[PDB]
Image 1 (cartoon, one colour):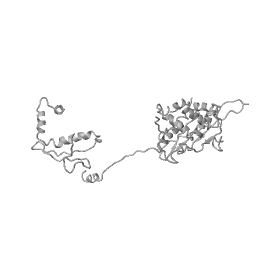
Image 2: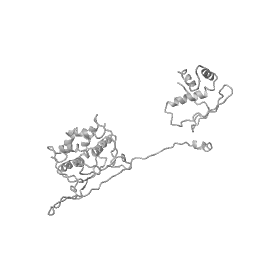
Image 3: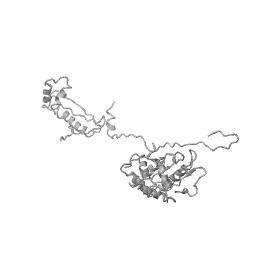
Image 4: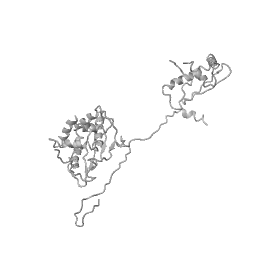
Length: 50
Length: 97
Length: 97
Length: 97
């Protein structure tokens, strides 16, 4: 603050700024995907697709 | 029955174990906590202490930030006989039960 | 009337205003808390927030560590009309008044 | 309750889901089908669509091959008003119920 006092005044009260945090968290979750493919499906599709 | 999740948005159950609280502004917007909450360090949680951890986190996020709970815990501290503050916590346990 | 000095051994009123709470073991000796408490950040406390700050520390230095207060705030959450944890604090205000 | 197995001998539940039907000779004479049957391609079969799959494979294996079912479905098509065969199937669903 910057207030106006008299010329013979008495030095008004103090003030400062303030700095604040944000804290923005990540370790909770994760996006994922699965397949479940066989071992014989991979074999007969190496000769039956163009 | 209190259903509850940790109130920070994307950091609800931490994989590190150290649940870090977001800073809430207590005492009617004059002060600031900036707490954390470390999980299990002296054992496990044995299916009852999940309910006690359910109320420690709720009283530390939704209560101290509130302005009607702090004016109700103030009037207990200005009663009679409540000095040497193991009596303040024991005059508060008779009200709640 | 509650009159006390904060329970840390040599750091009651710091010069910086960043009062660091001692680490305490709250969930019946399972979970660690590790808070701080930054002082006046939106002006001074005008002798009414100076009384509420005397009470917020008392629920934080002493009460969450105690094993009889946490059982009382456990049984409030097991009421038949307490869900949605902003009505959890309105269910313990009425006990404290 | 229907008890049923896929009619081709060594190929009942295939790995890839492409259940190749064995060819049947359908018109009691002169034709052949050589169908297949792909399994779950637009989801899964959720415990009721197994029963519909239990009856589609029975009407496709043991019914089109028969000579008294193809004569029973012949006489419905020579009925009254059974034209534009989206109504042939709707005049057959009234007989089955």
